[PDB]
Image (cartoon, rainbow over the protein chains, first blue to last red):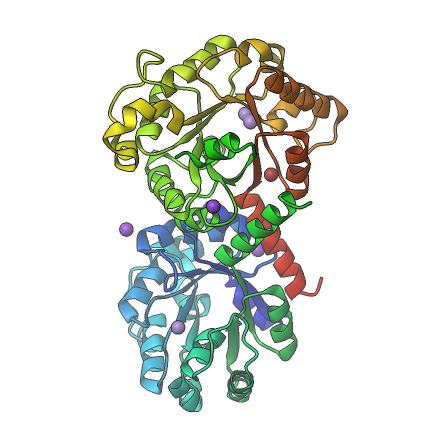
Length: 252
Length: 251
Ligand SMILES: [Br-]
Ligand SMILES: [K+]
Ligand SMILES: [K+]
Ligand SMILES: [K+]
Ligand SMILES: [Mn+2]
Ligand SMILES: [Mn+2]
Ligand SMILES: [Mn+2]
Protein backbone atom coordinates (compact mmCIF):
# COMPACT_ATOMS: atom_id res chain seq x y z
CA UNK A 1 0.00 0.00 0.00
CA UNK A 2 2.59 2.59 -1.05
CA UNK A 3 3.68 4.20 -4.31
CA UNK A 4 7.11 2.76 -4.97
CA UNK A 5 8.47 5.92 -6.47
CA UNK A 6 7.29 8.04 -3.54
CA UNK A 7 8.95 5.41 -1.28
CA UNK A 8 12.29 6.16 -3.03
CA UNK A 9 11.78 9.90 -2.65
CA UNK A 10 10.72 9.74 1.00
CA UNK A 11 14.17 8.14 1.68
CA UNK A 12 16.02 10.88 -0.27
CA UNK A 13 16.82 8.56 -3.22
CA UNK A 14 15.95 8.76 -6.97
CA UNK A 15 13.79 6.30 -8.81
CA UNK A 16 14.80 4.42 -11.97
CA UNK A 17 12.02 3.52 -14.41
CA UNK A 18 11.64 1.39 -17.51
CA UNK A 19 9.97 2.61 -20.71
CA UNK A 20 7.59 0.58 -22.84
CA UNK A 21 6.56 1.20 -26.43
CA UNK A 22 5.63 -2.36 -27.25
CA UNK A 23 2.12 -3.53 -26.22
CA UNK A 24 1.72 -6.70 -24.24
CA UNK A 25 1.88 -8.15 -20.70
CA UNK A 26 4.77 -10.67 -20.78
CA UNK A 27 7.68 -8.23 -21.24
CA UNK A 28 5.90 -5.76 -18.97
CA UNK A 29 5.85 -8.21 -16.10
CA UNK A 30 9.37 -9.44 -16.85
CA UNK A 31 10.88 -5.96 -16.92
CA UNK A 32 8.86 -4.90 -13.77
CA UNK A 33 10.55 -7.75 -11.92
CA UNK A 34 13.99 -6.18 -12.59
CA UNK A 35 15.64 -3.46 -10.45
CA UNK A 36 13.23 -0.82 -11.78
CA UNK A 37 11.13 1.14 -9.27
CA UNK A 38 8.53 1.99 -12.02
CA UNK A 39 7.72 1.10 -15.58
CA UNK A 40 6.35 3.83 -17.87
CA UNK A 41 4.01 2.82 -20.69
CA UNK A 42 4.33 5.24 -23.58
CA UNK A 43 0.89 6.00 -25.10
CA UNK A 44 2.23 8.88 -27.28
CA UNK A 45 5.06 7.46 -29.43
CA UNK A 46 3.82 3.93 -29.68
CA UNK A 47 0.78 2.00 -31.05
CA UNK A 48 -0.48 1.34 -27.47
CA UNK A 49 -4.14 2.30 -27.04
CA UNK A 50 -6.34 2.12 -23.92
CA UNK A 51 -7.41 -1.52 -24.57
CA UNK A 52 -3.78 -2.61 -24.62
CA UNK A 53 -2.52 -0.40 -21.77
CA UNK A 54 -5.17 -1.71 -19.27
CA UNK A 55 -3.78 -5.30 -18.91
CA UNK A 56 -0.18 -3.96 -19.03
CA UNK A 57 -0.90 -1.92 -15.86
CA UNK A 58 -1.92 -5.12 -14.08
CA UNK A 59 1.25 -7.04 -15.27
CA UNK A 60 3.58 -4.25 -14.06
CA UNK A 61 1.93 -4.13 -10.65
CA UNK A 62 2.28 -7.95 -10.30
CA UNK A 63 6.01 -7.86 -11.34
CA UNK A 64 6.47 -5.38 -8.49
CA UNK A 65 7.11 -1.97 -10.07
CA UNK A 66 4.96 1.10 -10.00
CA UNK A 67 2.87 1.43 -13.21
CA UNK A 68 3.30 4.78 -14.93
CA UNK A 69 1.95 6.13 -18.23
CA UNK A 70 3.22 8.91 -20.48
CA UNK A 71 -0.04 10.00 -22.06
CA UNK A 72 -0.65 11.11 -25.61
CA UNK A 73 -1.94 14.51 -24.44
CA UNK A 74 -2.55 16.52 -21.24
CA UNK A 75 -6.29 15.81 -21.20
CA UNK A 76 -8.06 15.48 -17.79
CA UNK A 77 -10.62 12.86 -18.77
CA UNK A 78 -7.94 10.65 -20.36
CA UNK A 79 -5.78 10.83 -17.28
CA UNK A 80 -8.79 10.10 -14.98
CA UNK A 81 -9.65 6.88 -16.81
CA UNK A 82 -6.02 5.72 -16.58
CA UNK A 83 -5.89 6.49 -12.83
CA UNK A 84 -9.14 4.53 -12.43
CA UNK A 85 -7.53 1.64 -14.33
CA UNK A 86 -4.50 1.62 -11.99
CA UNK A 87 -1.93 3.93 -13.49
CA UNK A 88 -0.12 5.35 -10.39
CA UNK A 89 2.14 7.75 -12.29
CA UNK A 90 1.30 10.23 -15.06
CA UNK A 91 3.72 12.04 -17.42
CA UNK A 92 1.79 14.56 -19.51
CA UNK A 93 3.32 15.99 -22.75
CA UNK A 94 3.50 19.61 -23.91
CA UNK A 95 2.94 21.35 -20.62
CA UNK A 96 4.05 24.81 -21.74
CA UNK A 97 2.25 27.24 -19.42
CA UNK A 98 0.98 27.56 -15.84
CA UNK A 99 -2.68 27.08 -17.00
CA UNK A 100 -1.75 23.78 -18.69
CA UNK A 101 0.11 22.67 -15.52
CA UNK A 102 -3.03 23.50 -13.48
CA UNK A 103 -5.05 21.42 -16.03
CA UNK A 104 -2.74 18.44 -15.23
CA UNK A 105 -3.04 19.02 -11.47
CA UNK A 106 -6.89 19.19 -11.76
CA UNK A 107 -6.99 15.62 -13.00
CA UNK A 108 -4.77 14.11 -10.25
CA UNK A 109 -6.74 15.17 -7.08
CA UNK A 110 -10.33 14.90 -5.87
CA UNK A 111 -12.17 18.00 -4.70
CA UNK A 112 -11.35 20.36 -3.15
CA UNK A 113 -7.77 20.05 -4.43
CA UNK A 114 -8.80 19.17 -8.01
CA UNK A 115 -11.80 17.93 -9.97
CA UNK A 116 -10.95 14.27 -10.40
CA UNK A 117 -14.19 12.33 -10.94
CA UNK A 118 -14.86 9.56 -8.37
CA UNK A 119 -14.94 5.92 -9.54
CA UNK A 120 -11.62 4.22 -8.56
CA UNK A 121 -12.23 0.70 -9.86
CA UNK A 122 -8.66 -0.58 -9.54
CA UNK A 123 -7.16 1.69 -6.82
CA UNK A 124 -9.96 0.75 -4.40
CA UNK A 125 -8.95 -2.92 -4.88
CA UNK A 126 -5.19 -2.23 -4.33
CA UNK A 127 -5.56 0.18 -1.38
CA UNK A 128 -8.94 -1.01 -0.06
CA UNK A 129 -10.98 0.78 2.55
CA UNK A 130 -8.41 3.49 3.38
CA UNK A 131 -7.89 4.57 -0.30
CA UNK A 132 -9.69 7.90 -0.32
CA UNK A 133 -7.83 9.10 2.81
CA UNK A 134 -4.49 8.84 0.99
CA UNK A 135 -5.56 9.08 -2.67
CA UNK A 136 -3.37 12.06 -3.76
CA UNK A 137 -0.23 10.37 -2.30
CA UNK A 138 -0.88 7.23 -4.31
CA UNK A 139 -0.30 9.06 -7.60
CA UNK A 140 2.80 10.79 -9.00
CA UNK A 141 2.25 13.51 -11.59
CA UNK A 142 4.93 15.11 -13.79
CA UNK A 143 4.51 17.88 -16.43
CA UNK A 144 6.69 17.46 -19.56
CA UNK A 145 9.02 20.32 -20.47
CA UNK A 146 9.96 19.97 -24.11
CA UNK A 147 9.56 23.38 -25.74
CA UNK A 148 11.15 26.82 -25.83
CA UNK A 149 7.96 28.24 -24.30
CA UNK A 150 7.94 25.71 -21.43
CA UNK A 151 11.57 26.67 -20.77
CA UNK A 152 10.56 30.36 -20.61
CA UNK A 153 7.65 29.57 -18.29
CA UNK A 154 9.49 27.10 -16.01
CA UNK A 155 9.07 29.12 -12.77
CA UNK A 156 5.29 29.60 -13.31
CA UNK A 157 4.91 25.91 -14.12
CA UNK A 158 6.77 24.89 -10.90
CA UNK A 159 4.51 27.29 -8.90
CA UNK A 160 1.57 24.88 -9.40
CA UNK A 161 1.02 23.03 -6.09
CA UNK A 162 -0.73 19.87 -7.30
CA UNK A 163 2.05 18.46 -9.51
CA UNK A 164 5.11 16.63 -8.13
CA UNK A 165 7.47 18.12 -10.72
CA UNK A 166 8.58 18.13 -14.35
CA UNK A 167 9.89 15.59 -16.79
CA UNK A 168 12.47 16.59 -19.42
CA UNK A 169 12.20 15.24 -22.98
CA UNK A 170 15.74 16.11 -24.26
CA UNK A 171 15.17 15.11 -27.88
CA UNK A 172 11.94 17.11 -28.21
CA UNK A 173 13.68 20.09 -26.61
CA UNK A 174 16.66 19.79 -28.99
CA UNK A 175 14.28 19.72 -31.98
CA UNK A 176 12.20 22.64 -30.71
CA UNK A 177 15.41 24.66 -30.04
CA UNK A 178 16.42 24.20 -33.73
CA UNK A 179 18.87 21.25 -33.32
CA UNK A 180 18.92 17.63 -34.44
CA UNK A 181 16.73 15.19 -32.46
CA UNK A 182 19.59 13.01 -31.28
CA UNK A 183 19.19 10.26 -28.73
CA UNK A 184 20.81 11.51 -25.51
CA UNK A 185 21.76 14.83 -27.13
CA UNK A 186 24.66 16.76 -25.56
CA UNK A 187 24.10 19.84 -27.81
CA UNK A 188 25.41 22.66 -25.64
CA UNK A 189 22.32 24.88 -25.75
CA UNK A 190 20.17 21.90 -24.78
CA UNK A 191 22.53 20.78 -21.96
CA UNK A 192 22.32 24.34 -20.60
CA UNK A 193 18.51 24.42 -20.89
CA UNK A 194 18.20 21.11 -19.04
CA UNK A 195 20.68 22.22 -16.32
CA UNK A 196 18.57 25.33 -15.85
CA UNK A 197 15.29 23.43 -15.54
CA UNK A 198 16.86 21.07 -12.96
CA UNK A 199 18.07 24.03 -10.92
CA UNK A 200 14.73 25.91 -10.95
CA UNK A 201 12.87 22.72 -10.05
CA UNK A 202 15.08 21.89 -7.07
CA UNK A 203 15.02 25.56 -5.95
CA UNK A 204 11.18 25.42 -6.01
CA UNK A 205 11.28 22.16 -3.99
CA UNK A 206 9.92 20.06 -6.86
CA UNK A 207 11.07 16.79 -8.40
CA UNK A 208 12.76 16.64 -11.84
CA UNK A 209 12.81 13.57 -14.08
CA UNK A 210 14.39 12.95 -17.50
CA UNK A 211 14.06 10.48 -20.35
CA UNK A 212 17.22 8.57 -21.17
CA UNK A 213 18.09 6.56 -24.31
CA UNK A 214 20.80 4.55 -22.52
CA UNK A 215 22.22 3.27 -19.21
CA UNK A 216 25.26 5.56 -19.53
CA UNK A 217 23.19 8.72 -19.96
CA UNK A 218 20.98 7.69 -16.96
CA UNK A 219 24.06 7.23 -14.71
CA UNK A 220 25.11 10.81 -15.50
CA UNK A 221 21.65 12.17 -14.81
CA UNK A 222 21.43 10.26 -11.52
CA UNK A 223 24.87 11.74 -10.59
CA UNK A 224 23.53 15.20 -11.46
CA UNK A 225 20.71 14.77 -8.94
CA UNK A 226 17.67 13.97 -11.07
CA UNK A 227 14.82 12.45 -9.05
CA UNK A 228 13.28 10.25 -11.75
CA UNK A 229 15.32 8.69 -14.57
CA UNK A 230 13.98 6.42 -17.31
CA UNK A 231 16.20 4.09 -19.33
CA UNK A 232 15.67 2.76 -22.01
CA UNK A 233 12.82 2.09 -24.49
CA UNK A 234 12.09 -1.60 -24.85
CA UNK A 235 11.96 -1.36 -28.68
CA UNK A 236 15.41 0.37 -28.90
CA UNK A 237 17.01 -2.11 -26.44
CA UNK A 238 15.54 -5.09 -28.28
CA UNK A 239 16.58 -3.87 -31.80
CA UNK A 240 20.12 -3.16 -30.64
CA UNK A 241 20.27 -6.54 -28.91
CA UNK A 242 19.12 -8.37 -32.10
CA UNK A 243 21.60 -6.41 -34.25
CA UNK A 244 24.42 -7.52 -31.94
CA UNK A 245 23.22 -11.16 -31.91
CA UNK A 246 23.20 -11.17 -35.73
CA UNK A 247 26.69 -9.55 -35.93
CA UNK A 248 28.07 -12.21 -33.56
CA UNK A 249 26.36 -15.03 -35.49
CA UNK A 250 27.57 -13.91 -38.97
CA UNK A 251 31.16 -13.09 -37.75
CA UNK A 252 34.36 -14.63 -39.21
CA UNK B 1 10.02 -16.34 -53.72
CA UNK B 2 10.50 -17.90 -50.27
CA UNK B 3 13.65 -16.12 -48.96
CA UNK B 4 14.79 -19.14 -47.02
CA UNK B 5 14.48 -21.47 -49.96
CA UNK B 6 16.42 -18.82 -51.99
CA UNK B 7 19.30 -18.97 -49.43
CA UNK B 8 19.35 -22.79 -49.69
CA UNK B 9 19.16 -22.66 -53.53
CA UNK B 10 22.16 -20.27 -53.55
CA UNK B 11 24.19 -22.66 -51.30
CA UNK B 12 23.94 -20.63 -48.07
CA UNK B 13 22.17 -21.17 -44.73
CA UNK B 14 19.41 -19.03 -43.22
CA UNK B 15 19.60 -17.07 -39.97
CA UNK B 16 16.23 -16.45 -38.31
CA UNK B 17 14.75 -14.38 -35.48
CA UNK B 18 12.53 -15.87 -32.78
CA UNK B 19 9.47 -14.15 -31.27
CA UNK B 20 7.51 -14.94 -28.13
CA UNK B 21 6.21 -11.39 -27.55
CA UNK B 22 2.99 -10.58 -29.57
CA UNK B 23 2.76 -7.40 -31.61
CA UNK B 24 3.70 -6.05 -35.03
CA UNK B 25 6.18 -3.23 -34.25
CA UNK B 26 9.10 -5.35 -33.06
CA UNK B 27 8.18 -8.04 -35.60
CA UNK B 28 8.66 -5.48 -38.40
CA UNK B 29 11.74 -3.94 -36.74
CA UNK B 30 13.48 -7.30 -36.34
CA UNK B 31 12.44 -8.45 -39.85
CA UNK B 32 14.27 -5.40 -41.31
CA UNK B 33 17.58 -6.58 -39.72
CA UNK B 34 19.86 -9.11 -41.37
CA UNK B 35 17.53 -12.04 -40.62
CA UNK B 36 16.32 -14.16 -43.59
CA UNK B 37 13.27 -15.32 -41.58
CA UNK B 38 11.57 -14.56 -38.32
CA UNK B 39 9.87 -17.35 -36.39
CA UNK B 40 6.78 -16.67 -34.39
CA UNK B 41 6.55 -19.01 -31.45
CA UNK B 42 2.89 -20.09 -30.83
CA UNK B 43 3.82 -22.89 -28.34
CA UNK B 44 5.82 -21.25 -25.47
CA UNK B 45 4.30 -17.83 -25.65
CA UNK B 46 0.90 -16.13 -25.19
CA UNK B 47 0.60 -15.65 -29.00
CA UNK B 48 -2.85 -16.90 -30.22
CA UNK B 49 -4.13 -16.96 -33.84
CA UNK B 50 -5.64 -13.44 -33.66
CA UNK B 51 -2.26 -12.07 -32.57
CA UNK B 52 -0.16 -14.03 -35.01
CA UNK B 53 -2.14 -12.93 -38.10
CA UNK B 54 -1.08 -9.27 -38.22
CA UNK B 55 2.55 -10.25 -37.17
CA UNK B 56 2.92 -12.31 -40.36
CA UNK B 57 1.97 -9.23 -42.38
CA UNK B 58 4.49 -7.10 -40.45
CA UNK B 59 7.38 -9.57 -40.93
CA UNK B 60 6.70 -9.80 -44.66
CA UNK B 61 6.61 -6.01 -45.02
CA UNK B 62 9.95 -5.77 -43.15
CA UNK B 63 11.39 -8.28 -45.62
CA UNK B 64 11.99 -11.53 -43.88
CA UNK B 65 10.13 -14.79 -44.44
CA UNK B 66 7.38 -15.27 -41.76
CA UNK B 67 7.75 -18.65 -40.05
CA UNK B 68 5.65 -20.14 -37.26
CA UNK B 69 6.49 -22.72 -34.62
CA UNK B 70 3.03 -24.16 -34.00
CA UNK B 71 1.59 -25.32 -30.64
CA UNK B 72 1.04 -28.75 -32.09
CA UNK B 73 1.44 -30.84 -35.25
CA UNK B 74 -2.23 -30.52 -36.23
CA UNK B 75 -3.02 -30.31 -39.98
CA UNK B 76 -5.99 -27.94 -39.79
CA UNK B 77 -4.07 -25.47 -37.57
CA UNK B 78 -1.16 -25.47 -40.01
CA UNK B 79 -3.51 -25.05 -43.04
CA UNK B 80 -5.11 -21.96 -41.48
CA UNK B 81 -1.64 -20.44 -40.85
CA UNK B 82 -0.48 -21.12 -44.44
CA UNK B 83 -3.73 -19.44 -45.63
CA UNK B 84 -2.85 -16.45 -43.36
CA UNK B 85 0.65 -16.19 -44.97
CA UNK B 86 2.91 -18.27 -42.77
CA UNK B 87 5.51 -19.39 -45.35
CA UNK B 88 7.44 -21.59 -42.93
CA UNK B 89 6.18 -24.17 -40.42
CA UNK B 90 8.10 -25.74 -37.46
CA UNK B 91 5.92 -28.45 -35.86
CA UNK B 92 6.76 -29.64 -32.30
CA UNK B 93 7.14 -33.20 -31.06
CA UNK B 94 7.49 -35.04 -34.38
CA UNK B 95 8.53 -38.41 -32.99
CA UNK B 96 7.69 -40.97 -35.71
CA UNK B 97 7.41 -41.44 -39.47
CA UNK B 98 3.60 -41.35 -39.10
CA UNK B 99 3.71 -37.94 -37.38
CA UNK B 100 6.16 -36.57 -40.02
CA UNK B 101 3.71 -37.76 -42.75
CA UNK B 102 0.91 -35.90 -40.92
CA UNK B 103 3.01 -32.73 -41.12
CA UNK B 104 3.71 -33.31 -44.84
CA UNK B 105 0.02 -33.86 -45.51
CA UNK B 106 -0.79 -30.32 -44.37
CA UNK B 107 1.81 -28.61 -46.51
CA UNK B 108 0.84 -29.84 -50.06
CA UNK B 109 -2.35 -29.82 -52.15
CA UNK B 110 -3.73 -33.02 -53.61
CA UNK B 111 -2.47 -35.25 -54.98
CA UNK B 112 0.77 -34.85 -52.96
CA UNK B 113 -1.01 -33.96 -49.68
CA UNK B 114 -4.48 -33.02 -48.49
CA UNK B 115 -4.20 -29.32 -47.89
CA UNK B 116 -7.60 -27.63 -48.22
CA UNK B 117 -7.74 -24.98 -51.00
CA UNK B 118 -8.56 -21.44 -49.88
CA UNK B 119 -5.25 -19.42 -50.06
CA UNK B 120 -6.43 -15.99 -48.91
CA UNK B 121 -3.04 -14.33 -48.40
CA UNK B 122 -0.74 -16.50 -50.64
CA UNK B 123 -2.99 -15.79 -53.65
CA UNK B 124 -2.46 -12.05 -52.97
CA UNK B 125 1.38 -12.59 -52.87
CA UNK B 126 1.71 -15.04 -55.75
CA UNK B 127 -1.36 -14.35 -57.96
CA UNK B 128 -3.39 -16.83 -60.04
CA UNK B 129 -0.35 -19.04 -60.74
CA UNK B 130 -0.02 -19.92 -57.01
CA UNK B 131 -1.19 -23.54 -57.18
CA UNK B 132 1.54 -24.69 -59.58
CA UNK B 133 4.24 -23.26 -57.31
CA UNK B 134 2.50 -23.64 -53.90
CA UNK B 135 4.68 -26.44 -52.45
CA UNK B 136 7.92 -24.47 -53.11
CA UNK B 137 6.56 -21.36 -51.44
CA UNK B 138 6.46 -23.10 -48.03
CA UNK B 139 9.20 -24.55 -45.82
CA UNK B 140 8.25 -27.41 -43.49
CA UNK B 141 10.51 -28.63 -40.62
CA UNK B 142 9.75 -31.42 -38.15
CA UNK B 143 10.96 -30.84 -34.59
CA UNK B 144 13.33 -33.43 -33.05
CA UNK B 145 13.15 -32.98 -29.29
CA UNK B 146 12.77 -36.43 -27.69
CA UNK B 147 14.66 -39.71 -27.30
CA UNK B 148 11.95 -41.29 -29.44
CA UNK B 149 12.55 -38.80 -32.33
CA UNK B 150 16.28 -39.43 -32.01
CA UNK B 151 15.75 -43.17 -32.34
CA UNK B 152 13.40 -42.76 -35.39
CA UNK B 153 15.45 -40.04 -37.12
CA UNK B 154 16.06 -41.98 -40.36
CA UNK B 155 12.39 -42.95 -40.71
CA UNK B 156 11.38 -39.31 -40.09
CA UNK B 157 14.00 -38.08 -42.63
CA UNK B 158 12.58 -40.56 -45.21
CA UNK B 159 9.32 -38.59 -45.58
CA UNK B 160 8.72 -36.81 -48.83
CA UNK B 161 7.09 -33.46 -48.36
CA UNK B 162 9.19 -32.12 -45.47
CA UNK B 163 12.34 -30.14 -46.09
CA UNK B 164 14.07 -31.54 -42.97
CA UNK B 165 14.20 -31.30 -39.16
CA UNK B 166 14.60 -28.63 -36.52
CA UNK B 167 16.36 -29.53 -33.25
CA UNK B 168 14.84 -28.35 -29.99
CA UNK B 169 17.92 -28.63 -27.79
CA UNK B 170 16.42 -27.71 -24.39
CA UNK B 171 13.58 -30.28 -24.68
CA UNK B 172 16.07 -32.79 -26.06
CA UNK B 173 18.46 -32.25 -23.14
CA UNK B 174 15.53 -32.63 -20.71
CA UNK B 175 14.30 -35.84 -22.29
CA UNK B 176 17.89 -37.28 -22.19
CA UNK B 177 17.90 -36.66 -18.40
CA UNK B 178 19.91 -33.43 -18.32
CA UNK B 179 19.25 -29.80 -17.42
CA UNK B 180 17.21 -27.82 -20.04
CA UNK B 181 19.94 -25.22 -20.59
CA UNK B 182 20.17 -23.50 -23.97
CA UNK B 183 23.49 -23.73 -25.84
CA UNK B 184 24.48 -26.57 -23.50
CA UNK B 185 27.95 -28.13 -23.35
CA UNK B 186 26.61 -31.43 -21.92
CA UNK B 187 28.48 -34.07 -23.90
CA UNK B 188 25.60 -36.50 -24.52
CA UNK B 189 23.41 -33.66 -25.86
CA UNK B 190 26.12 -32.15 -28.05
CA UNK B 191 26.70 -35.63 -29.46
CA UNK B 192 22.97 -36.21 -30.18
CA UNK B 193 22.71 -32.83 -31.92
CA UNK B 194 25.76 -33.68 -34.13
CA UNK B 195 24.20 -37.07 -34.88
CA UNK B 196 20.86 -35.65 -36.09
CA UNK B 197 22.73 -33.14 -38.26
CA UNK B 198 24.87 -35.91 -39.77
CA UNK B 199 21.83 -38.12 -40.45
CA UNK B 200 19.90 -35.24 -42.05
CA UNK B 201 22.79 -34.29 -44.35
CA UNK B 202 23.36 -37.91 -45.34
CA UNK B 203 19.64 -38.13 -46.29
CA UNK B 204 19.91 -34.95 -48.43
CA UNK B 205 17.59 -33.09 -46.02
CA UNK B 206 18.00 -29.76 -44.20
CA UNK B 207 18.65 -29.34 -40.44
CA UNK B 208 17.95 -26.38 -38.16
CA UNK B 209 18.63 -25.54 -34.53
CA UNK B 210 17.40 -23.13 -31.86
CA UNK B 211 20.22 -20.98 -30.31
CA UNK B 212 20.31 -18.72 -27.27
CA UNK B 213 23.29 -16.53 -28.30
CA UNK B 214 25.01 -15.23 -31.42
CA UNK B 215 28.27 -16.94 -30.36
CA UNK B 216 26.58 -20.33 -30.28
CA UNK B 217 24.83 -19.64 -33.58
CA UNK B 218 28.14 -18.76 -35.26
CA UNK B 219 29.39 -22.24 -34.33
CA UNK B 220 26.20 -23.98 -35.54
CA UNK B 221 26.51 -22.19 -38.91
CA UNK B 222 30.19 -23.23 -39.16
CA UNK B 223 29.07 -26.86 -38.43
CA UNK B 224 26.71 -26.81 -41.44
CA UNK B 225 23.26 -26.16 -39.93
CA UNK B 226 20.90 -25.00 -42.67
CA UNK B 227 18.54 -23.02 -40.42
CA UNK B 228 19.78 -21.28 -37.28
CA UNK B 229 17.62 -19.22 -34.97
CA UNK B 230 19.12 -16.65 -32.59
CA UNK B 231 17.79 -15.49 -30.09
CA UNK B 232 14.26 -15.13 -28.44
CA UNK B 233 13.03 -11.53 -28.23
CA UNK B 234 11.98 -11.87 -24.56
CA UNK B 235 15.46 -13.32 -23.57
CA UNK B 236 17.29 -10.58 -25.47
CA UNK B 237 15.11 -7.77 -24.14
CA UNK B 238 15.48 -9.07 -20.57
CA UNK B 239 19.30 -9.23 -20.77
CA UNK B 240 19.41 -5.78 -22.40
CA UNK B 241 17.28 -4.21 -19.62
CA UNK B 242 19.39 -5.89 -16.85
CA UNK B 243 22.57 -4.39 -18.42
CA UNK B 244 20.96 -0.97 -18.77
CA UNK B 245 19.91 -0.98 -15.13
CA UNK B 246 23.40 -2.10 -14.01
CA UNK B 247 25.02 0.66 -16.12
CA UNK B 248 22.58 3.29 -14.75
CA UNK B 249 22.92 2.25 -11.09
CA UNK B 250 26.72 1.87 -11.56
CA UNK B 251 26.65 -1.74 -10.35
BR1 LIG C 1 17.01 -18.65 -24.79
K1 LIG D 1 -8.98 -0.93 -28.67
K1 LIG E 1 10.91 -4.07 -9.47
K1 LIG F 1 15.71 -9.00 -43.50
MN1 LIG G 1 7.17 15.48 -27.56
MN1 LIG H 1 10.84 -27.72 -27.32
MN1 LIG I 1 9.01 -29.06 -26.80
